[PDB]
Image (cartoon, coloured by chain):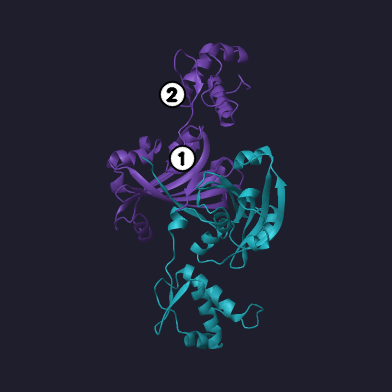
Chain colours: A cyan, B purple
Amino acid sequence: MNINKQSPIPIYYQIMEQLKTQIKNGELQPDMPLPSEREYAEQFGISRMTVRQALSNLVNEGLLYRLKGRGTFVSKPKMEQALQGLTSFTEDMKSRGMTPGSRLIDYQLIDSTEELAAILGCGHPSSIHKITRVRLANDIPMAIESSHIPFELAGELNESHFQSSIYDHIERYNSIPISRAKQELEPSAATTEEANILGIQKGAPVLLIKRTTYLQNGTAFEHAKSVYRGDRYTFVHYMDRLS
Amino acid sequence: MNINKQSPIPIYYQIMEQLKTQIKNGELQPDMPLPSEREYAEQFGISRMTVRQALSNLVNEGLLYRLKGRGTFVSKPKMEQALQGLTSFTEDMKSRGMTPGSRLIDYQLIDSTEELAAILGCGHPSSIHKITRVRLANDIPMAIESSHIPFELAGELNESHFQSSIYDHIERYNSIPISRAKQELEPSAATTEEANILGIQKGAPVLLIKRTTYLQNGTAFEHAKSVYRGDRYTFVHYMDRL
């Protein structure tokens, strides 16, 4: 583990990021104690309060837990929804021990076409949200997502929606659960503009994910197309044989 | 549809494949009648028996059905298992209206390794089948598959097994149904060897698929790694929110 004191990136943030890597490395195993706050302080020659800030942040994110008078430990993850269910990008990143975020690239409220109407099974003519975001994990681009949503199913949208979970909004606005999705996966090569935004070379491996998601209603509320970085993302799921 | 009579590819084969294309894009709709032998015969300027040969082979593959007379209808394929369950390559290709095939690249009976023991949950030391095939759809390379299978769960394997469905053999051999799989998918670029065998350019998009498959009783019988042509293959599946 390596701290660079002269870097613009705050010491505490350097520590969080590396500890997060050590957890996915398996250098820090679940339910196993972490070095003490003073040990870390001594091992890097830093303030104990900076260590506290890092550790405390990871506890508050649910990545670590603390037992009063007995230290800090790695938390067991929550995997039912990730492997056996359907996750939003936000839940997906958390299942992987990553911190999700989003930055808006483009927002348009567009007129329905027969093609989009067919896919969403919405009204034509009508209004459809078109939301283009960079999805981040640990402040680093992970995907570019273009998302179409019937206006009636989401109402008026703004920056506060774009920077959090759209799935959470949908369920609260409609007071109906999300129930299922059709998804298609295709491999591809990053275009110049996808590559530049994503932080990878032109032509680098990329996963194209097309998803239509449904309310318990049977009503489609979203059709989305995403490009995920190949170096950082693999898709994982269980399948059951029907009989 | 066009027909090249001077081609080494048999006419009835050229017909089969262009009818398959018509279906795959909905120029022929499910459960809608096709033209008769005479109409096709006249269309291409060929024997009626050649058209019949193309249609009858398609009936046998379940791509078409009959009801009465030689007259033929587009089949409406079962998609439930493909989209919501778990299919072998064989069933997967059929759900797409493609004809699956297999050719052996390599076979070895290998000794158990620590990593492989932990994956399949099998014994160590033990013997493991290592089977590398080119998986074909309509006589054209689709995937390269490398699968590890504990000897005891398959017994002795030969060409008759490799050129057919492993999944079916393992169910017949064991009298226990296949239950579930864990799959991981990652995009990549074809190596030189992979690209050559697949019929694509070096560095062309491929999909890496890693699958561990279990029997109804919980035993893992297969750990497979595959490379799929990005130009022919899309992965499709429904997911339910818990």
Indicate the position of residue A175 as horizontal and vertical percent values.
Answer: 53, 54
Q: Which residue is mark 2?
A: B60
Relative to A111, say whether A192 is above or below. Answer: below
Of tags 2 and 1, the one toward the viewer is 1
Density class for disc 2 (Cα within 10 Å; few <14, some 14-19, many ≥20) is: few
Density class for disc 1 (Cα within 10 Å; few <14, some 14-19, many ≥20) is: many
Horizontal side of residue B120 vs B73, given as left or right: left
Using the rendered image of the protein, determine whether residue A38 is visible from the camera's viewpoint: yes
Residue at screen point 59% across, 42% down:
B231
Amino acid at the residue labelled 2: Asn
Horizontal side of residue A83 vs B14, given as left or right: left
Image quadrant holding the C terminus of chain A, namely top left
What chain is tagged by disc 2? B
Using the rendered image of the protein, determine whether residue B157 is visible from the camera's viewpoint: no
Does dot 1 land on a helix, a strand or a loop? helix
Can you tell which mark lies on residue B82? 1
